[PDB]
Image (cartoon, rainbow over all chains, first blue to last red; front, side, top):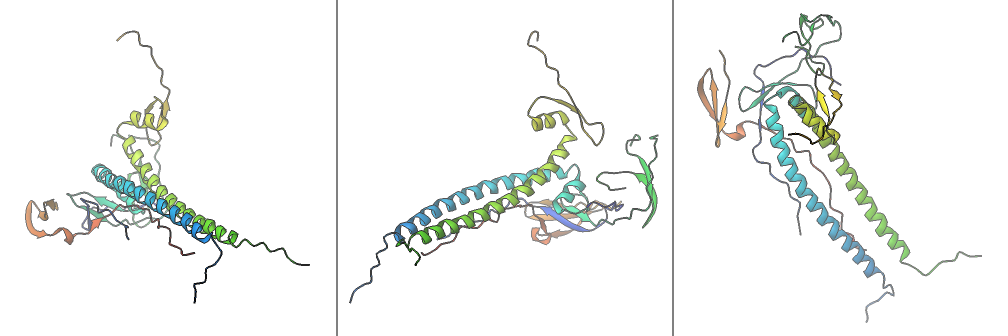
Length: 30
Length: 123
Length: 89
Length: 49
């Protein structure tokens, strides 16, 4: 499940940004 | 010529029962979907707010796997988590971080000494 | 001998209507239960995270009754709450 | 020392390094994290008896 890890890394890597406005899905028809 | 009427006056009423019950269930599903949409919108804010305190735990739960992160600005950068093998653990029985987390050492991978973290993660 | 057929061609179609509607509702309930499971898993993390700031308020809401707590380590210890009477303020 | 900050303002992202800016990227230039645990219920079908 949760293995021991000694990464402790804060260098350059993949970036991700939080969304600001979630679009609501729709399914109406007919 | 003539049209072949069948003496089954029950087919039309069975269709109404199915059609009537279908219309109401589909309306309930639409009402429930709208409520879930608003709740998920609020939960997004509560997740962003908590990320400013302990980014590692919040990011790990979102991904579902152990990762590492560091918020050096408004955009959070995710690093990769390198694991280690259970080969050497040290548990000193004295604390003298203000001696809060225990001074521990490990080996294999690399070897070093440090303070035990949280969720079976070592510095 | 013979089998006693009844001239009721509607019983079979009524059974299909009930059976068809039963199959779809039970599938919707399963889909909804899975979504609620994931939400509750996330809410567990948000509760543990907030306990590190104000343990007393978080613990009281979870229990539903006024209690006292103090986080002296990774395991939270719950003490008992002794009340007082409105006699002097 | 090294200081990667890259704030965001309006419909624009300004990237700063070592207390200095050198690039500008649109919002779509960076992937967006999503947390939308959602139902997948399906409306019940239509049947002609």
